[PDB]
Image (spheres, coloured by chain):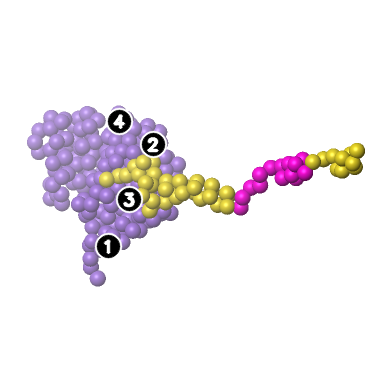
Amino acid sequence: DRVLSLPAVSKNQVLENVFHTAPKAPVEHLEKMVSANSKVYDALNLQSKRVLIWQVKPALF
Amino acid sequence: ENDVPAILKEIDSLVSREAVSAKEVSDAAVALTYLQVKANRRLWGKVLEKAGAAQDYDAASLTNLLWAINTGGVEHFKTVAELAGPAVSLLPSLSPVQLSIVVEALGGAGVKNYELYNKASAVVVSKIGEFKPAEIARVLYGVAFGGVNDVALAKAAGKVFASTEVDSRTAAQALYALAKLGRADKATVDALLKSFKKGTESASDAAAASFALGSLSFKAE
């Protein structure tokens, strides 16, 4: 019964109770918010190619 | 030292920026009429867009903006008809000449705003001595073309134009207002047609008097 003197909690249970959640990358914030502020740029810049100022306040010619 | 298209580009960039307040719109419009810039429709569109975008408004900038809109002969019913709220909020703080310009101006575009014309006709018949008769003819033009059949102001104008000898253009504008109103008061129209003898500085007011007397069928003067 030498196995009952060993710690009963496995190494697998340590690795799954210690590294439980996949950690959040530091670049995820930059990638996601830059992909969304690209749409903020494209809609609302006055120098963006597909700007939404002429669809919203149309013109007066 | 004297350059028209470069100052058109200066007004163009002055009106194309984002935070233009109402005084800049008003003097850009007045400067755009005084240079007689009917050839540029986009510039008048930019000035009228910024006039619709403005929220501050006093008597002077609103009055010069409306004067410029009607002297330049530009028409856009949306931005002119949305300038009558600034008028009715600022109406007791208006001068009688300023009330004259804004009521003739909002009447010429055809703004159906009955509160403005009621509260302006009540002002001009509550204090009738304040008003020089050109102001009377301009308010009469605006109340006639705004779609109210106001005969109280028409009778007050008849009393003023029979008592006071008036201008040629003043009488012509009063004749045009009476012709749209369809009133044909010979006691008023005679006192207006007697003013057409001192030589007329314009031809459009003589043409308007001819159309007015044709619409009323008095006879050719």
Q: Nearer the viewer, mark 3 or mark 4?
A: 3
Q: Nearer the viewer, mark 1 or mark 4?
A: 1
> What's the CA distance linking mark 1 and mark 3?
15 Å
Q: Position of residue B33 (x, y in %)?
A: 25, 53
What residue do we see at 66% from left, 47% from top?
Answer: A23
> What's the CA distance linking mark 2 and mark 4?
12 Å
Label 1 or label 3, whichever comes before in sequence order: 1
Q: Nearer the viewer, mark 2 or mark 1?
A: 1
Label 2 Cα neighbours within 10 Å, binned few <14 / some 14-19 / many ≥20: many
Label 2 or label 4, whichever comes before in sequence order: 2
On screen, residue A36 above or below B8? above
Which residue is the site of mark 2?
Answer: B116
For the residue marked with disc 2, what is the amino acid? Leu
Label 3 or label 2, whichever comes before in sequence order: 3
Circle number at residue B147:
4
- The reply to whether label 2 and label 4 mark residues of one chain is yes
Which residue is the site of mark 3?
Answer: B47
